[PDB]
Image (cartoon, rainbow over all chains, first blue to last red; front, side, top):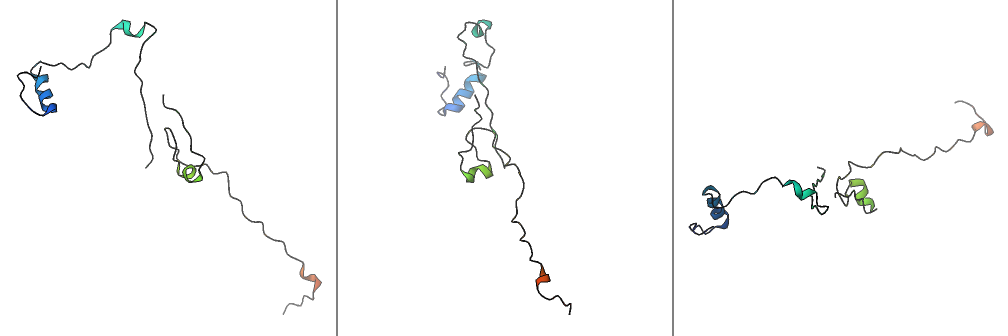
Length: 52
Length: 52
């Protein structure tokens, strides 16, 4: 990828690729076996509270 | 995994609610108010009591 894309800025050049099907967004679900092998790095959720 | 944390036992932070982890407190509680006791009076009948 980024071969025909000549744009210098990294962010924009990446953005060109998404439309042109070169790269693909990987926001995607996980295969069922990933959370069963007893070694499953399960993502964590964090929260914070501040007072004004 | 979002530890509770606690104030550093430094009176400056404990009143303000500045904590070490998450969920800064609203503020301290209110256990009440104490006031200096009123001294009692010595009876005036020792000296002559003539209302002028």
